[PDB]
Image: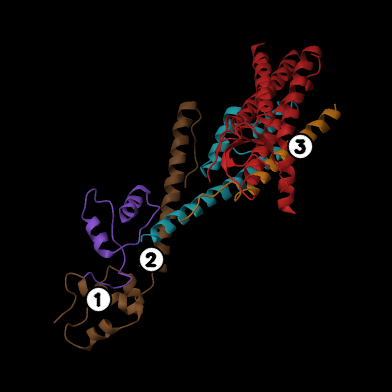
Chain colours: A cyan, B purple, C red, D orange, E brown
């Protein structure tokens, strides 16, 4: 909802919208980014790109933490099986 | 009583272990509902007379 | 037309939900004391943002206060005690509704509607911080209560109003382009 | 055994995210405000 | 790997959005479970001393019936060995060889 806002709020760019980041597409681009998936669009503005950048960093950490913590669960569970 | 000790193992959902004579531990392991196990070697040695 | 109707109703709902949340006391169903010998007894309690009200035992209904203060750790406790962010969302949602009301009166200044959009979007962001700062400071079982869910639900109802307001701004400026 | 990561562990990634969203809107609004003073 | 064209409708996106969640978990389970294999099997310590055998119950150990290698455990006052004597005595099948 922040990505959509920035991209489409300003009325000095609607020469036909300025980009393709509408509300519906914004959800799609934020779900795709989180799932480390492919591309359909990429922000071309400054404000929009800031949101993208922080979102990509958030995903990285979170996705890394999941995998990292998942291995911990498996390894600790696989080493404990009882003197 | 030991009977209480055995019942406490069976009702505690994996969160209690009971220390007792090997003879009793072995007997219960062969009784229905077959939900207990003896683990480890004996800690000491004695006899009945 | 009907789009403005949703915004108004949705804005009121968001505001109402959040206010109940803050004011109520059913945020964290924990198990603690509610009374300031050398004895004690922990019974199930339904905590809140300000008071820890017991719901079981001989002290059923006694609402004690919470000593949030029993430099990273200090800052967290300081913010969590005053509820700056949760209360800030209340202030922002209230202000965002005034703007929508001000619209009908001043129908020649499109920036009245876009202001509501920013307040509502920014009100949601404050709500997120409040949830995070309440779950981090708070950390034997727990289960959040209906009051905590009115906060979370308010966020959603405030982000949806936010996008709706931004569409109204966009849409209005689109009609101006046509007239030009 | 192991525990499940709590919000307290991954806490600075939601402040950055929320802080970044705030910064993004600010940049956008200042650009729009500047353009609105140039008309 | 793969980024060319993505769905653009509501129905197609729903399909692609659950598929994306599926892949994430599945591709994070392989890596995570693979690490456990490469970690658990690395931590494994090769058999050493007698204390290790006493704790273990998988690999059986047996002395000879008549000789000094059985008297030593029978009379041993060391717990790490006294434990083994008790098991080896009544254990079946008889590990004691001829």
Figure check: C8 above or below D6: above
- Which mark's residue is nearer the viewer, 3 or 1? 1
Label 1 vs label 2, nearer the camera:
1
Please name the residue that numbered disc 1 is placed on: E61
Q: Total of numbered circles in the picture? A: 3
Q: Secondary structure at mark 2?
A: helix
Q: Which residue is disc 3 drawn over?
A: D26
Q: Mark 1 falls on what kind of element?
A: loop
Residue A13, relative to residue A37: is it above or below?
above
In front of the other: C120 or C147: C147
Characterize the local packing of mark 3: few (<14), some (14-19) or many (20 or more) Cα atoms within 10 angstroms. some
Report whether E56 appears left or right of D19: left
Chain holding disc 1: E
Where E92 falls versus E3 (above or below)?
below
> Mark 3 and mark 1: span between their CA atoms?
74 Å
In the displayed orientation, state which residue is furthest to the bottom: E68
Secondary element at tag 3: helix
Residue at image mark 2? E41
Residue that appears at 38% across and 49% down: B12
Question: Looking at the picture, how far across and down is residue E12, in whole percent?
Answer: 46, 30
The quadrant of the picture occupied by the C terminus of chain A is: bottom left
Residue that sits furthest to the top in the current view: C1
**Viewport quadrant of the N terminus of chain A:** top right
- CB of mark 1 within 8 Å of CB of mark 2? no
Residue at mark 3: chain: D
Q: Chain of mark 2?
A: E
Whole-percent x and y of residue A2? Answer: 66, 34
Q: Marks 3 and 1: same chain? A: no
Residue C49 seen in this snapshot: no
x%, y% of residue D17? 66, 43
Q: Pick the residue in front: B43 or E63.
A: B43
């Amino acid at each position: 909802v922040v990505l959509f806002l920035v991209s489409r709020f300003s009325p000095y760019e609607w020469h036909q919208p300025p980009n393709e980041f509408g509300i519906f597409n914004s959800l799609w681009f934020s779900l795709g980014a989180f799932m480390q998936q492919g591309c359909d669009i990429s922000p071309r503005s400054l404000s929009g790109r800031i949101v993208g950048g922080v979102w990509w960093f958030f995903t990285l950490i979170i996705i890394s933490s999941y995998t990292a913590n998942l291995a911990a669960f498996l390894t600790v569970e696989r080493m404990v099986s009882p003197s | 009583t030991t009977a209480e000790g055995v019942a406490r193992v069976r009702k505690s959902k994996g969160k209690f272990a009971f220390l007792l004579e090997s003879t009793m531990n072995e007997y219960i392991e062969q009784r229905k509902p077959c939900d207990t196990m003896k683990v480890g070697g004996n800690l000491d040695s004695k006899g009945y007379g | 037309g009907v789009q403005m109707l949703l915004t108004i109703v949705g804005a009121f709902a968001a505001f109402s939900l959040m206010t109940i949340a803050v004011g109520t006391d059913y945020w964290l169903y924990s198990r603690g004391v509610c009374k300031t010998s050398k004895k004690n007894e922990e019974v199930m309690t339904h905590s809140g943002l300000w008071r820890t009200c017991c719901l079981e035992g001989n002290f059923k209904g006694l609402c004690k206060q919470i000593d949030h203060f029993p430099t990273a750790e200090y800052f967290l406790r300081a913010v969590r005690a005053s509820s700056i962010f949760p209360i800030l969302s209340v202030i922002l949602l209230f202000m965002g509704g005034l703007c929508i009301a001000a619209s009908e009166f001043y129908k020649t200044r499109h920036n009245i509607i876009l202001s509501a959009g920013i307040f509502f979007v920014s009100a949601g962001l404050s709500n997120i911080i409040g949830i995070i700062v309440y779950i981090s400071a708070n950390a034997n079982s727990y289960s959040y209560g209906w009051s905590f869910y009115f906060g979370a639900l308010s966020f959603i109802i405030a982000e949806m109003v936010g996008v709706l307001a931004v569409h109204m701004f966009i849409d209005r400026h689109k009609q101006l382009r046509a007239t030009a | 055994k192991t525990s499940a990561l709590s919000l307290s562990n991954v806490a600075g990634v939601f402040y950055i995210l929320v802080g970044g969203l705030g910064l993004a809107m600010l940049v956008a609004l200042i650009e729009f405000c500047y353009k609105s003073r140039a008309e | 790997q793969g980024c060319d064209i993505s769905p653009r409708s509501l129905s197609g996106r729903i399909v692609g959005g659950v598929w994306w969640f599926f892949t994430l978990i599945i591709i994070s389970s392989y890596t995570a479970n693979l690490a456990a294999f490469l970690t658990v099997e690395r931590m494994v310590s090769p058999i050493e001393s007698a204390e290790d055998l006493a704790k273990q119950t998988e690999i059986a150990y047996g002395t000879l019936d008549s000789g000094s290698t059985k008297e030593f455990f029978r009379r041993s006052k060391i717990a790490v060995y006294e434990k083994m004597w008790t098991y080896m005595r009544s254990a079946e099948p008889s590990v004691f060889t001829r």
